[PDB]
Length: 81
Image 1 (cartoon, rainbow, N blue to C red):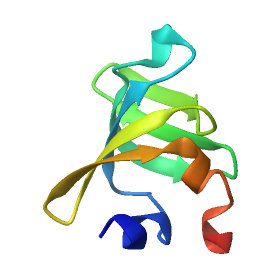
Image 2 (cartoon, rainbow, N blue to C red; image 1 turned 90 degrees about the vertical axis):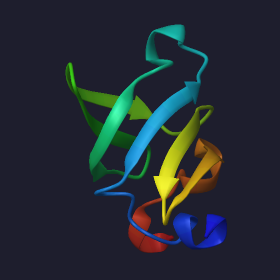
Image 3 (tube, helix red, strand yellow; image 1 turned 30 degrees about the vertical axis):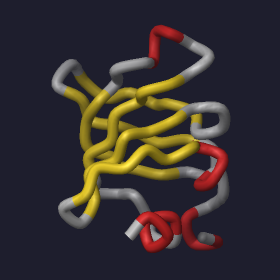
């Protein structure tokens, strides 16, 4: 499911920033409400947060599995995979 995850729009999934050059972003957790070519708009308990994909690592809850995904892998428009 790790491979299938890269091929779909992450909208609707729960994700958590587990690694980032900006410490301020580590821990940002919530539901992806939008995905752009370079960012993820995440709805958190504290509010909406936009986090860049490149250089970040995300913990993702998908298909009963919990995976660590490097932002570089999804740093493309979702429709382009």
